[PDB]
Picture 1 (tube, rainbow, N blue to C red):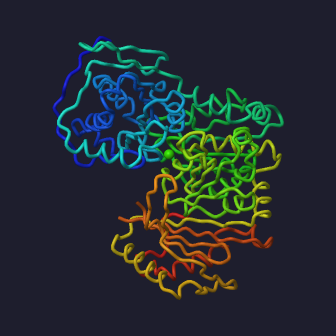
Picture 2: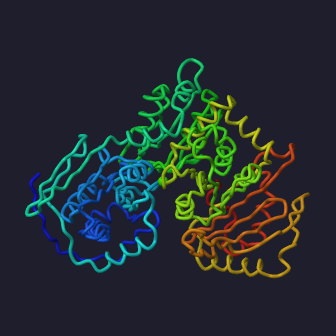
Picture 3: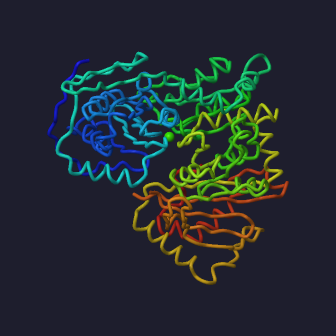
Length: 559
Ligand SMILES: [Ca+2]
């Protein structure tokens, strides 16, 4: 642990873009491309001014996928050589994305490097990702990721301590003396769960939750971490501390290949959990994605809570949670394609509702302005301003808190909610890997059609019901915090009855078609969703001429 600093000549790569969720490549790319990881790590660290490196701490950890520990060792060797004073690293390299955000904010780190590719498959033939978060605990913004990219493109050398090796498996402080450097390099290995659990212990009423989850008359739960990073969090918090029986923790051992499956929480990737819930034995089920910031919520018999409804239900019962009883509710937000269910709650309770373009930064900005308490995305995303990433296990404890106060089943809570606010039937059609020319033509033609002065007021017949266009545009957002203007964020068809159709191209092309059908009638709100959605789906396909432009007669995926 007495080690030399050396300078390594390297050759730059041209494709190392950090994106909004990190640099992601196949594992084999990282393995076969000389200094691929080294170059990128150096580029991140070179964004930190030399004068500020010794007093800086970086938080480092990841989702447990293959190659993670090797990448972490590399980050330590390079951080040390570059004069970064300290790393804080989760035991075994493990930290969920929400735990990283938690720890950065708690210890006032300059940021963190997260070894995750989120839900993407891992293993020797899978994907790997390197994500950079800054001092507010959230994703590095474009100005920073721009700078990292620029540096990586022309880098000709990096600094490294080749003989430095960190023991990731044992808790505590390891110090490294660097040759011809006065100050030591320090690594603190922390328990992967402790800080995050201590945070949750202050947010939620663990006494109430222990009462709910323990004993003969307990709420019966099945919580599926999909062999990813949230596993130990489930075991240590829900089972060990809150007393849920050990069987409650499903697929809660992190695996380097996530068990050979894709850790994304939806009805088909988490098919095993759904089949478990179908037996009527359990009251509540949930699944998480690989790095822990997405969640799916299930009730008895595998009743599916739509993510757009989940955030609305949490909003409508938000003072069941001690944190909000103390902060108050500062605002609500959803991404524009997410259903308008949250809006109904916000309008009725007179709380601001922010409708943002797709992406974290819009939520993070509003939170940093003390204007946003609770946010949701239709893509299984739920969060609050307790940190600056979405948080799947948090959403689960929010649901458990509501179940404890309401003393009703998941399905009955939703039925009561629909009765009170009306129901926003919702689905998302994905058309994957469509020919770009056809997708682009479809969008440009539709947008032109929508811009015509006569389009507003146009009527579309169902069947029975007539839909009337209230507004039609290509969504634009002026950020109230950083002043940026986001344009071309999705074609919106907004109907006078509270329903909407939205088309986006994904950022082969992917078309995402979102259908939001609002119904107030008692005779309609408990019908089957794809049946109730069929009229607007028909209207959407006809006005867009999607089949004509793409050759597709059906979506690839329906959620
Ligand atoms: Ca994720």
